[PDB]
Image (cartoon, rainbow over all chains, first blue to last red; front, side, top):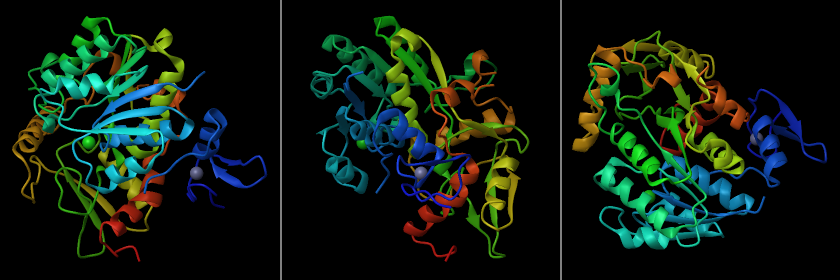
Length: 42
Length: 318
Ligand SMILES: [Cl-]
Ligand SMILES: [Zn+2]
């Protein structure tokens, strides 16, 4: 499995977007707390 | 509740950049100071909407500081020894912040002063941050002090000092350092976790963190363990080699040398703990509560290391 946001394939816990798509613990947790998708470099 | 305006300096630095991307994203307005508008990160920080930059030096430039804190409710301050004398810079910023009178939470990134806990000397790029910390407290600024664990992304195969993951000929990686092989060290994934953690601290407010020191480290691994992380995360064989002295393979600046020499003595010759403060002698507890979506050395090594190397000009992974 992979994260729709950060594409990581390594994470302690997988989460799902309010639709059902896989997000990593961090990305999923970040959105849940702040309301927006976790922003990345580059 | 409401998103506030945050003041930051050294925007291109790893701690700040992390906070800026995250904060801007969730809705906060950012007022940051950069040394130069030239550079990838700089241009990037420029591409983010609610981010205002002020190009100029920090040393003896109280005007930049005044402007920086105008309308600011929050501030994350992490200076570099390169910008000049950290104590004087760190004190001018604190004075400006107080003169602005609108700062509700002032987070300063501080570092220990080892000589205060043993015949150990003072790590030059670390010690002065403790003086600024005390001065922040002295002004009465509602504050919180964060102590960053060693960056995960300091690692590189390139001949950079202290944290080189040199690519030997036998298709393996060796890491040369003074740090004791079996002594757990405090690590931190700058890009991935500084931002979110800082946000949480702000969301909590000084009503919770005012006066506190927070070890910004989400996992403690010994050098052997760090290498076991890479070796188990890249199919390669990775070994740690303890060397009494740090290897400088590239023309670096003065300040940076002396800093390394201090490290050799403190960790190599005295085996003195990274965070010699008693409260820091589990340390990672406060951090992991502040933010649980942390990236450990295994994920960093398997998901980021290979990428940073590539864009850096290497194909060993391909
Ligand atoms: Cl900068
Ligand atoms: Zn993710």
